[PDB]
Length: 150
Length: 149
Ligand code: MET
Ligand code: MET
Ligand SMILES: [Zn+2]
Ligand SMILES: [Zn+2]
Image (cartoon, rainbow over all chains, first blue to last red; front, top):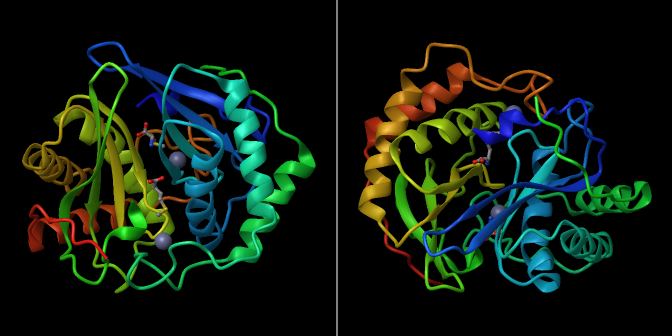
């Protein structure tokens, strides 16, 4: 598990970081990015808020970046993982994430996909908190974080 | 897409192909919905799903080749897994069952729990994670069709 090899005490959130790159048999690269909102072990995003962030960024990352495969919350609740079909491009992903965070901070419309039909825990959302976490990231400023291994 | 699955019609627990993307050279990335609980009838506690993530990240990789990622769903009723390869729900179901047996029997320290290796090392619950694995095996897994809204 490559996740456990990053030295979580040495990164500086918020940031974007290439977490890993894998190739398919023919040679296509699948890049995975760590979209980190909070500093590891200094607090966590509430489950309702990260659930709303997942629904919003699922769509907003796709709006600003091609080849997105998935946007998922991390179990540690300090960030999200995003998988993209394409060569590593930390700067491009940082710009996309910034654009998507502006969309997220200003999202005043209903949360996309929230209903008993469309979501598996439809009552567990918190748009006010998700918007504020996006604004906090923008307020602090993103950067491309080097992977510091253990 | 995730919002097009009719969540009131699926039958947890199950394994379901949630999507498949073709890569530029003709290869495929498959996405799987590894559902533990019935949508909207309760959720896995955050600490418990954080432990399930640490355990299944390694156990799924022990039983299935090409795993790219194993992550918890924001709705906390299951996990999403992305795999390089053609769809193979039967193979993923068999791999998930093996991984759940490993999880249910995990009586050693949770892997990766420290300030160095985890972003929230104080939020774990091995006992709850092992019981969730047991409950899925007790109910029994099956391949769930995608019922669209
Ligand atoms: C539940 S919103 C969709 C999130 C999913 N992990 C993906 O980006 O497709
Ligand atoms: C924090 S355990 C590892 C997590 C990551 N989702 C993986 O599948 O690579
Ligand atoms: Zn949801
Ligand atoms: Zn962790």
